[PDB]
Image (cartoon, rainbow, N blue to C red):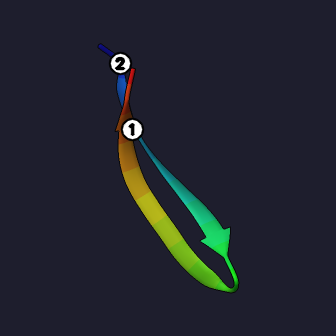
């Protein structure tokens, strides 16, 4: 139940989102 917010870079845009495990 670990949720983290990661910000990646896709095609020059910052894609940041919270994933939960």
> In the rendered image, which residue does mark 2 sit on?
2
Identify whether 19 is placed above or below 14: above
Crowding near pointer 2: few (<14 within 10 Å), some, many (20+)?
few
Residue drawn at x 39%, y 55% as measured from the top left = 17
The one of 10 and 4 positioned closer to us in this rendering: 10
Identify whether 7 is placed above or below 13: above
Residue 16: image quadrant is bottom left
Marks 2 and 1, the one that precedes in the sequence:
2
Q: Which mark is residue 19?
A: 1
Asked whether the residues under the numbered discs 2 and 1 touch, taking CB atoms below 8 Å apart as contact, a structural biologist would say: no
Residue drawn at x 35%, y 18% as measured from the top left = 2
Is 15 on the left or on the right of 8, as rendered? left
Q: Residue furthest bottom?
A: 12
Identify whether 4 is placed above or below 18: above
Is 1 on the left or on the right of 4, as rendered? left
Task: Provide residue 9's location: percent of width, then percent of height.
Answer: 65, 70
The one of 7 and 20 positioned closer to us in this rendering: 20
Crowding near pointer 1: few (<14 within 10 Å), some, many (20+)?
few
Q: Residue furthest top?
A: 1
Q: Which mark is residue 3?
A: none
Q: CA distance from mark 2 to mark 1?
A: 8 Å
Identify whether 17 is placed above or below 20: below
Task: Provide residue 7's location: percent of width, then percent of height.
Answer: 53, 59
Residue drawn at x 61%, y 61% as measured from the top left = 8
Residue 11: image quadrant is bottom right
Task: Provide residue 6's location: percent of width, then percent of height.
Answer: 50, 49
The quarter of the rendered structure image containing the N terminus is top left
Q: Secondary structure at mark 1?
A: strand
Is 21 on the left or on the right of 14, as rendered? left
Q: Secondary structure at mark 2?
A: loop
Residue 12: image quadrant is bottom right
The quarter of the rendered structure image containing the C terminus is top left
């Amino acid at each position: 139940g670990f949720c983290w917010n990661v910000c990646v870079y896709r095609n020059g845009v910052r894609v940041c989102h919270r994933r939960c495990n």
